[PDB]
Length: 324
Ligand SMILES: [Zn+2]
Image 1 (tube, helix red, strand yellow):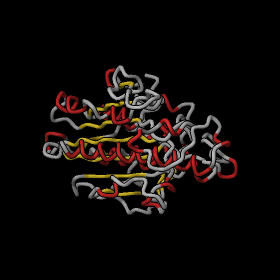
Image 2 (image 1 turned 135 degrees about the vertical axis):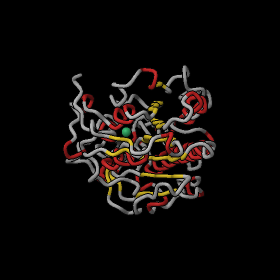
Image 3 (image 1 turned 60 degrees about the horizontal axis):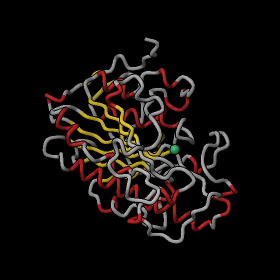
């Protein structure tokens, strides 16, 4: 087909009509720094809603595959691992979502950031939706920049769960998160906790604390979005076994040594551009997460996903996952 396969041997050991069906939300983040998370020692409570969630596992030692929203995302769903990962040929490799779609799991990708980078290309166009425009995202008139909001991705998922009744389901929500240099645009007035913030076009011209405040506000918005995801998943506890996974595609630099956005090559990228937060919540002791401070990378994503849907592929039975 011109596709290079890696998991043709993959097999789902237990099916939806052998046990309770499983519904999972994978929230793909952007620009979130692990060292700006309270659970990892940050001095501000940037995730106050997740702090009150029972069964929520935080991961403090996760490193990203790359430093950009073009390099890390295809690697997050790749089978190869960042060592063997090549970005020029990633679009053509079989990835975890291809494998899961083959095994009967409903894949759904809602994107409020840019695109899937190619992860959803081999899948029918009816499974990818653009939520950056008001065409699909119902929440775009809550701020004076008229930017569509991440929580708009939650509206109308009950109908997807209804149409796919009794199916294993995986839902990727691609966050706008903490992107771009205009951090002050990324959140609504409900989250303007820290002040002042930087409105400037040039980050170098900002006062450092203003930039920090804007970034932390956007982190508050993300915290709220993840929490609302978990609540939504709770509205389906009765019929499905539910779980939520959050990873950021990379970190961000905020003036450390005059460095200000992301994008630097891994060989020279500072520590802040690769340390990302990772969260995992499950209603059920069905899955038991690995230890908090286990040293992990994006290579843990693809095993995790497979483990969630009881899939066995030969390539990734030696891999560290987020669950045991
Ligand atoms: Zn990014």
